[PDB]
Amino acid sequence: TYEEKLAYGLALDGSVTLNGSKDLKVPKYSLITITGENNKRYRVEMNQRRYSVSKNQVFYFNPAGLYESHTFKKLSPYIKSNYSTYVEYFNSHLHQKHDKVTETLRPDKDKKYVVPITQQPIKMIFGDNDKLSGFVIPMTNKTELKKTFNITKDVWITKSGSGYFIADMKEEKWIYIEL
Image (cartoon, rainbow, N blue to C red; front, side, top):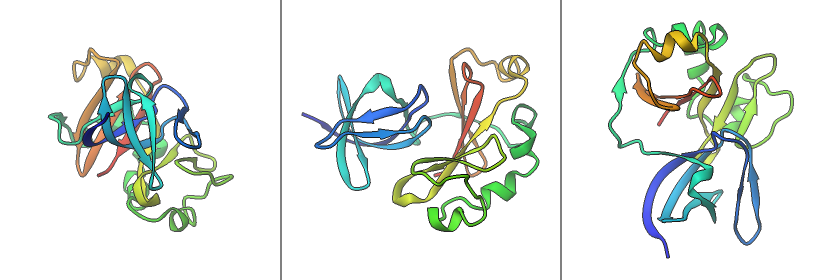
């Protein structure tokens, strides 16, 4: 019924409902752990329960894949100054528990999976074991970006330092994901 697999999925297109014994709605930009596949659906696991979703509703992300690499400096022109200038301040919080992280990156109102930081156009992404896994960050100078790295697709992935950058061209947002 399912092929045994391990990978990640990103709710790039919008919120998603994970079908299970009880259904579960996850916000736009959620990082989801894929545990199986079958032509029509992904098996995904969230908080140690199995759910299922149709493949077209999440963007498939394979960390083992081959991607180009670029430093942060060559990318910072196209990332919002708010995060760019202070990149190491934010990344400083990565891989830490949700309750610790929200002590300093404070949200207006805490929520699971994806959390807006107060007074910033930045969202925090919580992955497995409720640890900070990455950020949703605005894109600047799109037209200048897409012809600098010769990007032709709607969604562009690259390695960068300790992590990955995923550029959703249509929504003009970056997802930085680490590990």
